[PDB]
Image (cartoon, rainbow over all chains, first blue to last red):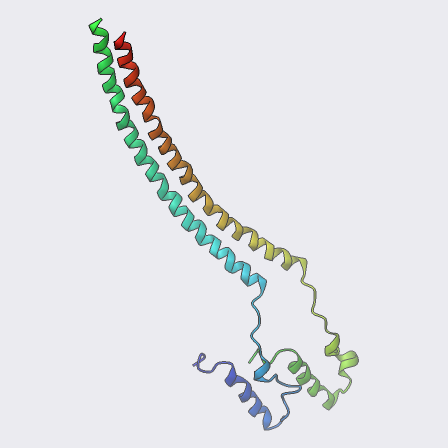
Length: 100
Length: 100
């Protein structure tokens, strides 16, 4: 029931409880609902929120860096297979020496 | 009820409690509301804010390795494909030798 018994309900209940003994509460005892502006969040909470965002960004950036290296690895695997022509080129070279 | 029940209402409520027995609040039993300057934040909590701000900067800035390292990774693979011209250069050189 706490969401249902929010903040606007709490004021006038305390008023009525007080109204039976202390009537004029809007000037010294309680603040009117029309002027209870919500408090701006503290900078400590803001930096905690921002630092948590950095924490997942590092986790996210960890994943892509942890994934990106695999692409380089597969590129390396093709490279040795690319060099297979160089060994095949040696076949031409050794028999080229033979014709002289 | 905390928003409406801030400081002036509670001070007035505690004031209203007082004059029934002890009238003299605003002079020495209590301090007048118009002279309550907010306390300057202590350096301990000032640093703690820039403490968390420092670590959350790292989380954002730790991620840029995961993207930057892959930037170099693709360049090396591009360089590997660039060196294929040198492999092709040997084909010209080998038959250039056979020309003589």
